[PDB]
Amino acid sequence: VRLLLTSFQHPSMAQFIGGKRVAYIPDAARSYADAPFVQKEREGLEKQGLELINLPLSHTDLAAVETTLNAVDGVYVAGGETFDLLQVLRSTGSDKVITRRVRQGLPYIGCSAGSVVAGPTIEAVSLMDSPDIAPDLKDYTGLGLTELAVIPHASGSISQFPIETIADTVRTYGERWPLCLLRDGQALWIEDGEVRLLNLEHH
Amino acid sequence: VRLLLTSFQHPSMAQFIGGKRVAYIPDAARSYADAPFVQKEREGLEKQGLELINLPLSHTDLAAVETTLNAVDGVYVAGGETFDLLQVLRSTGSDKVITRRVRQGLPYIGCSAGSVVAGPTIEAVSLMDSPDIAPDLKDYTGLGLTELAVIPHASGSISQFPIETIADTVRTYGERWPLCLLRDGQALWIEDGEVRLLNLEHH
Image (cartoon, rainbow over all chains, first blue to last red; front, side, top):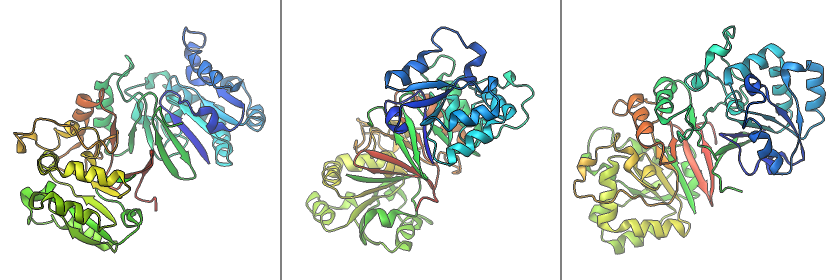
């Protein structure tokens, strides 16, 4: 079981995958699909020599979700609106498909919202991403691929998520949940239980 | 270079040292040396089969600090008042002695205040430990054995350091310093650059 949970990507993503073909799951950002600078995430992976296989879960039946995830060397779950991404994952039902494939050894890279849904819950980022985008979302449980609750952009370097609200997130969820503050540039390299916390320079 | 930085100890401390003899540096808690439950830290290491060599830096000339640190399998820097511990380390001058010995491969275990002084600064815990205990302490720079700024007891489970002030610490120091929230039971196993974040169960 291999996870690479980044706040906003990491230079060793390509080495983590160990291959060239990565399924790119964009649904977290479907709410502004063709908005300027939404492609910056795909350029980061492409700049490292990865060829991306787009896999929009909202527009794919689960049989084809299964077929792509068995023809790729890894899967990448892009950032965006965390609550809408879990709405997709639970409604589509690919939450079971992706989780099953990840546990069989398919390496999983998370970025922002992709890193949070890998953990036990998305409730700890409700001061970061709006929960109102999924008003019919009852259960906030994540995929459970990791027990660590990633809080991305922990430096306060994004205007939508300033250090005041990251602090509010710690005040609100720090007691029950094992919060992990990730700054942009950092990533969690998780491999068969061992959790390595990497900075930018670790490659 | 081997560090094990715990919030409040970790079950694998003995395995980290790889030997039986550990120099126990108690000065962070000299301000209440014989106070009830101050010995709980020494029992934790002793319960794991470690024989502790007490090394109070306030009462030891640097030549003997050097001699003990060369006859032990590792060094343990106990919790207490972070600002008084750095006052000791800088005034005694053992900050250079310990740092030199750690870089030569002497394994270093930090607990609370011992884990914070290993990093770049102690200023990020000034809402946790009082800086007034060292009014003549000019420079807040740490030992620099790690670049990660450990914030211990991050769960808010200690009455003196509730989740509100850990949140205030993130609001106050989160932008400049690479804050690492450690909950009691967690520890950072750092070995030749690689930083592993361990939970209680990782042993």
